[PDB]
Image (cartoon, helix red, strand yellow):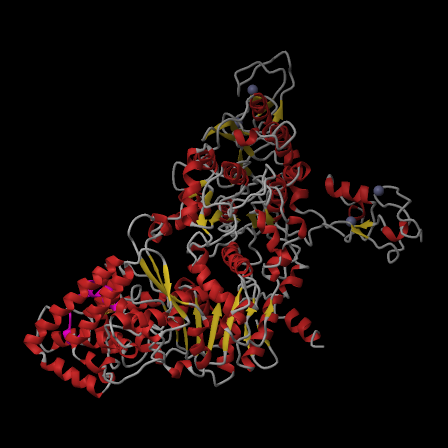
Amino acid sequence: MKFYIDDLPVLFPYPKIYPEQYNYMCDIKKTLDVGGNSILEMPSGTGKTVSLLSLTIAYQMHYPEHRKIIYCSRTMSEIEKALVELENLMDYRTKELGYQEDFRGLGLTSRKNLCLHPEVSKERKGTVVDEKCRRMTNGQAKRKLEEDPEANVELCEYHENLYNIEVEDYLPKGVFSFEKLLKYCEEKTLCPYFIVRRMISLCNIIIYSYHYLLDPKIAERVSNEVSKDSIVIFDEAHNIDNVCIESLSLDLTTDALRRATRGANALDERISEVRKVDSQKLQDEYEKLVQGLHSADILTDQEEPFVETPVLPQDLLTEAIPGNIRRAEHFVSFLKRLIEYLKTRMKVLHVISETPKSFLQHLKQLTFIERKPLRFCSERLSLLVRTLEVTEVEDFTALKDIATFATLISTYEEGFLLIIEPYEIENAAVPNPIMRFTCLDASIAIKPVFERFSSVIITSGTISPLDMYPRMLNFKTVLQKSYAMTLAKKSFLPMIITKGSDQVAISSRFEIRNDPSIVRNYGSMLVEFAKITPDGMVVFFPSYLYMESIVSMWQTMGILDEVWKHKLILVETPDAQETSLALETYRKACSNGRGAILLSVARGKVSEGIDFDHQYGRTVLMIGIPFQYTESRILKARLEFMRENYRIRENDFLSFDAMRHAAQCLGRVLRGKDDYGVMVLADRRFSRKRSQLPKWIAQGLSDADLNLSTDMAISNTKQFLRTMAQPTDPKDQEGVSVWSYEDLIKHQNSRKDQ
Amino acid sequence: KKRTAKKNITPYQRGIIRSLILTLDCSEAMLEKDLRPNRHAMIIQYAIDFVHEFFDQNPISQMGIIIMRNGLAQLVSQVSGNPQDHIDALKSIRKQEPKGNPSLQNALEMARGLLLPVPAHCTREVLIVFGSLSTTDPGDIHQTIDSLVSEKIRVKVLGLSAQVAICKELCKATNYGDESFYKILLDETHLKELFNEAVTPLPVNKINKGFTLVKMGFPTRIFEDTPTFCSCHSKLVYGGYFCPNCHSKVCSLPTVCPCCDLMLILSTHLARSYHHLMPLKTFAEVPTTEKFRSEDCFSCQSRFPXXXXXXXXXXXXXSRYRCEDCKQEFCVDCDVFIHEILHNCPGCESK
Ligand code: SF4
Ligand SMILES: [Zn+2]
Ligand SMILES: [Zn+2]
Ligand SMILES: [Zn+2]
Ligand SMILES: [Zn+2]
């Protein structure tokens, strides 16, 4: 299609369009005109990516100013979905117009999946794979390689052929999807990691996980050339406020404290051994500290940086000498004085949430170490370690967390919280204290990204209401509007099973345990679906531990064989590797004749990134209300902070947040308007939260569907499937919800110009 | 408010000389009380109807039957041109009851090799009656899917009031990638029409393939009764026929000769396809007022056509189904029955 929004061609890759899309198209350009925030709700059943990319890509190719576009998704899995979608649209944009791209657009996932060196790629741990190639292709290791001819230092050689051919230009013209990128890079024996690392200043659009925008330790290479005058795009960003606070979160364990002593004592050996050999550089680095923060070679580091910037990207940084901490022996001494004080603060017999100030003052009372120099731990460690040119990190892995933490808490106050549990309640009565620490307001990290740009886009099919987030992140949008699914057919049956076959108000809030009155009713309720439902059916527990709780007794119950006698059952596994193998086989079985049934957690990772088409998404299950206070009052602590900071209480936020995570899972049942699937839910309180739903979801929910019985619901979904299974192809009223190819959008919307 | 196909793209190559072995499920799934006796017994009732009608509408085709019981498929009828052997088989199968589960792949391959001896002109096709939601496959179905499509055998199947994506894919995969063959039921009459539309040949757009001529002869009836003697069954036949070439006393059968193996047919089967080959356009219901034609039926004598300004009775409609080619009307009862039974448009027949 090629229509206009009164200013720009719209090279829409599909012949068909949708009424939401043009309304989506109407607002995106309108928002694009006035760079703001404009939080909008677009139904996930429609593919917003097409409406997303098409108007934006044209906008850059029509308006000649915004040469850089930024999209931040939740998962790199979404990135490759966007990567091919852009690639297809880029092909289509060329297809409709010829060759008018000259465009650079690539994803960004990690070094782990982009380090093409097989040995480094073979390693499992993401830290090591990063660290290995960091060491394998290091600014100093290559010196140990180039200056001293030796086999001691090897290289990825992908970074080298990067420096040979790749660091003169870009990859020729492709908008490389991850498969296409990896296929190309491997044939060029290239490193897509270092490629995008240097391609930061070259990609006309960049797609990556929110963390590269959010996580300052990886949101630190930010170049204002691609950032300042760019547009920021967010979808499904509702479950990111937690991520933001998670990005500032930090859990500690006395074992790691001993690991810290393991590293910190090893530092004493490391600094002493080089001191006998070459302390002159260390003395020279003291002068490099005497001149300042040694930004000459603590930032100008091709592959040198040991400690990254865990704090926000150098906003709250001082650069003077650290007084006496200039000496490494002194530097470790306060650190060694600290870790034991930390241990002395870790050994608390009960749970204590210590204020950042009082705890710091308490430290000062115990170990008189000043706050401002304490932030220098991160820079000093990154500085010192490379000067030590250590050959290992595992002993020092605990240390960078301290360099993270000690800088963090010394930088952060009255927006963060240090809390020292004496153990974990799930394994209480044993000594396992955690010195848990995190932020409280998510907007704190959002404020710099708020500050840096005006044109920012946020979208979700789940966000409801669209007002908590402006309250939460303390910002003003332009358009706070929700889109409804223009469907002339049901295509999904929202079902609230408050009452079971027993007509019992059934819930997950009662306990995190089993009661067969509710549970066996649930088990009996579930099995009838296995017979009637086709391949594709998933459950979402409120908690993984709660998930396992119900599993064993149902396994003990005879309920287990019949569903196997009906379909295939695949579990959620703590390792995603087995889970992935389950997932593909589940989809394979879903693609296969033998039916497949799944089971997950509403907080599980599947609800985060994994979508399911018509066949793959057929019958979603919400196992009770997804609730999170199974854990401690750290939720309440932030919530109490939330309650005092914002006039939002627990349950209101909880219902908002729980249904947000509930709706987070439910968005994965749909692929397009061709897709469909009944949306069953089983909890007594589900009837109350009819308002908390997103509009189209709430619109799709009739009031007659509340507190339904499973038996009556079984009849309800019974007819739905056959009707949907029936080839409902009117081909005349479809154009009402299709806005027939290049005509109705041209005709109707231009008619609707009044 | 009309439920009609916009146009009928019949005009050319369809499935006429057919080799269909429909496969049934005989499982606990067919045992359940979804239909009044059950699925299976009503289905066996339903299935019986099509057999003769298949041999009625398509006497030029051959057919056997296979079922699937207890995770295993079982052939239950030989591919033949006589309904009776197939017909009598179901009577035992009627008195037989479905059991266990169906094995799709067992049916997949048992039927697959079953259709190997079929000639090219005899069109290979399979239809499935399935009630469960999962299969019983000894191996890779997609391999068998690959094997079947490599054999160039399009297939339509009809599951129960539900959908199976691979079955939706299979009917797609079998039929040149065109998915119009996984239609499922929602009602017994809606199931009855499935039989009714099944007897029709299958034109969509046949790829330009090798088209083969056919040579045979007509049979010549035997007259004597007391001379009872048979050769195709070594019996005594109180009346029979004679092969055009082998010249064997053969009982009444439009089948192939048993001695020199040539098809024996008189005239009837041939013209059955002809009205199928070139059907008519539906008699267009002429308007209530814009027609203003003779106030009577054309094929029949239905003087009443509307109600003449009778509020809504006349504003309802006008039973004026008019064939376009003849430009002559027909009462709906006449016109529908015409297109139902005998195309033979008298207005078009008269010239
Ligand atoms: S040089 Fe490239 S391929 Fe080798 S480990 Fe480093 S990033 Fe990976
Ligand atoms: Zn005989
Ligand atoms: Zn003969
Ligand atoms: Zn008539
Ligand atoms: Zn006519």
The spot of residue A620 in percent (x, y) is: 52, 49
The structure residue drawn at horizontal position 32% and vertical position 81%, both measured from the top left corner, is A317
Q: Is residue B8 left or right of residue A83?
A: right
Q: In which quarter of the image is residue A296?
A: bottom left
Which residue is the extreme one toward the top?
B226
The structure residue drawn at horizontal position 48% and vertical position 85%, both measured from the top left corner, is A64
- Given residues B221 and A45, the one toward you in this image is A45
Q: Is residue A199 left or right of residue A87?
A: left
Image quarter hosting the C terminus of chain A: bottom right
Q: What stretch is highlighted in magenta?
A: A386-400
The spot of residue A151 in percent (x, y) is: 10, 68
Is residue A193 visible in this depiction of the protein? yes
The spot of residue A350 in percent (x, y) is: 34, 56
- Characterize the magenta stretch by its predominant secondary structure: helix
Indicate whether B20 appears above or below A479: above
Is residue B215 visible in this depiction of the protein? no
Quadrant of picture, ligand 4 = top right
Which residue is the extreme one toward the bottom?
A291
Image quarter hosting the N terminus of chain A: bottom right
- Given residues A206 and A382, the one toward you in this image is A382
The structure residue drawn at horizontal position 61% and vertical position 60%, both measured from the top left corner, is A696
Count the labels in the image: 0
Is A397 part of what is drawn in magenta?
A: yes
Indicate whether A160 appears above or below A643: below
Is A133 part of what is drawn in magenta?
A: no
Q: Is residue A411 left or right of residue A159?
A: right
